[PDB]
Structures are given as structure tokens and as C-alpha cells.
Image (spheres, coloured by chain):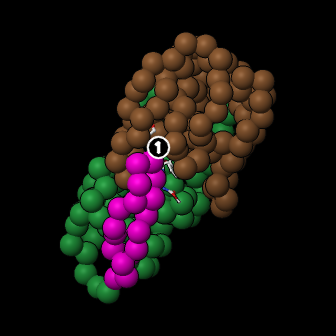
Chain colours: A green, B brown
Amino acid sequence: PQITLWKRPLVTIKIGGQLKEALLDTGADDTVLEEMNLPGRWKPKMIGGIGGFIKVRQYDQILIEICGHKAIGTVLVGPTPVNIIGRNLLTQIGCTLNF
Amino acid sequence: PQITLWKRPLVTIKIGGQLKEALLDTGADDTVLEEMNLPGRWKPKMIGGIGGFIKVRQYDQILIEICGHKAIGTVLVGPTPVNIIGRNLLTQIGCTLNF
Ligand SMILES: COC(=O)N[C@H](C(=O)N[C@@H](Cc1ccccc1)[C@@H](O)C[C@H](Cc1ccccc1)NC(=O)O[C@H]1CO[C@H]2OCC[C@H]21)C1CC1
């Protein structure tokens, strides 16, 4: 679809069998989700934005469905204020910016 | 144009008569630029991100050209790690997400 930017570009995602709301974020290299208990091994990581860094758990090869479009990649999980879909998964669903 | 997301969506902007590099960021409500000398009145403001809050100067009704498209709006100036163009100006240049 086409998403305008008058409001935060929030969409429904399906991950680990659960539905969540997430922000499509072209300014994010990586995808960061609010605290959730995903199964499997993970690696510690630190992610930075405005204000500093937070500690996250990095999970590899996680499947996420974003408005019916499937993507598979690295998902970071930690105390983020909002679920963020980053470029690593937005490239996979064929997302572009247009103006 | 149409911009894919394999690389960071960095563009050249013109502000206060100066050229800078900035990230087109659909996950940002507001536009935040690194420390710089902008003309005009300004107000102290606080903006929060993934790591916490930073102190910024809010400049209102600032002209900025983003890849040839003129926007006039609010620009925050402060210790951000990267220059970010947020939705407040992306809407003015007609930017949408498409997938
Ligand atoms: C490699 O480094 C990265 O990719 N870092 C990513 C990251 O932080 N990206 C941000 C831009 C960015 C890019 C590189 C370095 C610093 C800043 C932005 O895209 C996402 C962020 C989401 C958000 C956070 C708190 C509350 C609401 C929304 N938005 C934001 O901070 O916006 C500020 C300014 O506008 C205001 O509205 C919303 C909050 C306010 C993190 C996700 C992986």
C-alpha cells in the first residue's frame, strides 16, 4: 500500500505468533521490538539513537509479517519505547520512499 | 524520486544558506539537526529518542531545501548523532512510504 506521513506510520506486524503495532522507520538500520520472550539463542547488543544507547537481545533469522508481506532477518528486543521496523526488513518487503 | 532502503536514505539539504547531509526518517516526528549557527529567535526544548532525552533549540518557520523541494517549518538543533529530516517536513515535500 501507500502510507502517508501525517501520522506516525504505524502498521500491524505478526511475529512469533503474536500481532503487534510497529513503526515503519527509514531512519533505523535495524528492527527493535519491545520486550517479549522469544525462543532461541540470542547475542547481547547495544543500539544507539537520540539520547544514547540501550541494551538489547539480538535474535537471528526471525520471521515477521508486515501487512501481509513476509520478511526474515535480525530482530533486536529490548526496552524500546516503540516497536520499530528498520531498513533490514523494509528492504525485504520492497518498501521505498517517494516524493 | 523513488528511494530504496539498501543504504541509509541520506540526502543533501540546504539550510541557512549552507549545505548538509541528512537522513530522511519516517520514524521521527520532528526534524533534528546537529549543532549549527542558525539565524532567528529560538526556544529551549527537549526531545526524546531511543536512548533518552536531549536538549535542543527550537527554531520556527525555518526554510530548508530537501533535494530541491522547499519546506518551511520547525527545526530542532542539538547534540543529535545524525541530521534527521522528520515527518513535519517530509509531509511538506509530499513524501510517502510505498510497498
Ligand atoms: C544505527 O542507528 C540507528 O539506526 N538507530 C535507530 C534510531 O534511533 N533511529 C531514529 C533516527 C536516528 C538514526 C541514527 C542515530 C540517532 C537517531 C528514528 O528513526 C527512530 C526513533 C524511534 C522513536 C524513539 C523514541 C520515541 C518515538 C520514536 N525516532 C526518533 O528518535 O525521533 C525523535 C525525533 O523526532 C521525534 O519523534 C519521535 C522521537 C523523536 C534505532 C532504532 C534502531
User: Is A25 left, or right, of B95 in this rendering?
Assistant: left
Q: Residues within 10 Å of mark 1 (few under 14, many from 20)?
A: many
In the rendered image, is residue A66 in sight?
no
Residue B74 x/y as whole percent:
53, 21
Circle 1 sits on which residue?
Answer: B27
Residue B50 against residue B94 in the figure, above or below: below
Instruction: Please identify the quadrant where the N terminus of chain B is shown.
Output: top right
User: Is B4 left, or right, of A29 in this rendering?
Assistant: right
Residue A38 x/y as whole percent:
25, 75
Q: Residue furthest front?
A: B37
* Three-letter code, disc 1: Gly
Residue B55 against residue A21 in the figure, above or below: above
Residue in the picture at 41% in, 40% down: B54
Towards the viewer: B22 or A36? B22
User: What number of labels is visible?
Assistant: 1
- Location of residue B32 by image quarter: top right
Q: Residue furthest bottom?
A: A41
Towards the viewer: A92 or A80? A80
In the rendered image, is residue B61 in sight?
yes
Towards the viewer: A80 or B7? A80
Indicate whether residue B67 is drawn in magenta.
no
Towards the viewer: A34 or A50? A50
Element on which disc 1 rests: loop
User: Is A73 left, or right, of A58 in this rendering?
Assistant: right
Residue in the picture at 42% in, 79% down: A60
- Location of residue B65 by image quarter: top right
Residue B37 against residue A32 in the figure, above or below: above
Residue in the picture at 43% in, 64% down: A47
Residue A81 x/y as whole percent:
29, 50
Q: Main secondary structure of the magenta part?
A: strand
Ligand 1 within 8 angstroms of badge 1 C-beta: yes
**Which region shows up in magenta?**
A42-58
